[PDB]
Image (cartoon, rainbow over all chains, first blue to last red; front, top):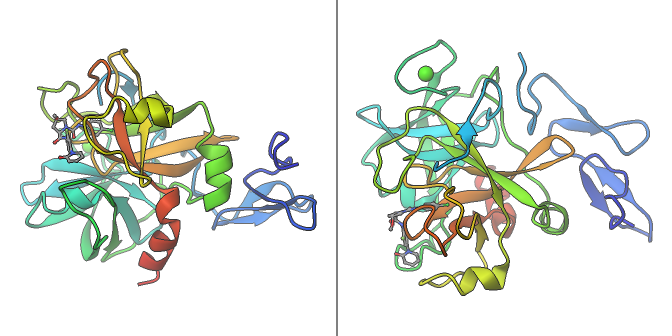
Length: 51
Length: 234
Ligand SMILES: CO[C@@H]1C[C@H](C(=O)Nc2ccc(-n3ccccc3=O)cc2F)N(C(=O)Nc2ccc(Cl)cc2)C1
Ligand SMILES: [Ca+2]
């Protein structure tokens, strides 16, 4: 269920073949566990900056 | 912005400021990528010529992080009309690429359905800008931000003396003295999800500011993702 805490996805969540498929915004790659979204470079979109 | 708090260092990196040839700010905008800025259509008629400023938090000076970028193309939604203020959205292609850094980074564009079922359903959104701090005040000199609650759609129509279209959405407080204002127009309305901020609205209009029984009216970004995606390829 994408309805349950977002199917444990970091960002986008879809329900294909009656399951769960995570994806990310441009600039991020889908992590190995297929849930987390890893930033492609410094200053990824959507993150407040620290440096 | 009326109420809210000051944008601390690195807090609102996607904020963009449209400045007139006199270098005075007049509208907000949101950084989408190194070349594109998202703003309000009604902000266009508001200036003969204009540039975009990024990395600024205090207009009274230059701390070194600020950067000016000239506009190469102004993509105004053709269906926008001041009579209804419907389709209040515009995309700007900059002449030179933005350099991401402290206080300078784009907000994320979400996917339609996901944003509508997950972002728009959130408890609150965040609006920011250098706009007036009061209805009859002056252009604020400090970048501000404000957590604005998403408002019931019906409760939104019952309070508007104007037509609220599907391309619009209410955010704000019924009586608490906080809201966006003039000058914040075109600015970002972002929603946070697991510490990632997605652009959800464009500051559009309001009958005054922070008025009891009134809300802030924002352009629904989800209703224009396709149009935005098409605008960024050319
Ligand atoms: C009285 O208002 C001052 C003047 C300025 C203004 O001109 N507002 C304004 C614009 C368009 C319409 N309008 C709507 C539908 C059809 C026709 C039409 O004319 C009505 C309006 F009142 N304003 C403002 O922009 N405040 C503002 C508040 C909250 C947020 Cl989020 C963003 C901005 C406050
Ligand atoms: Ca400054």
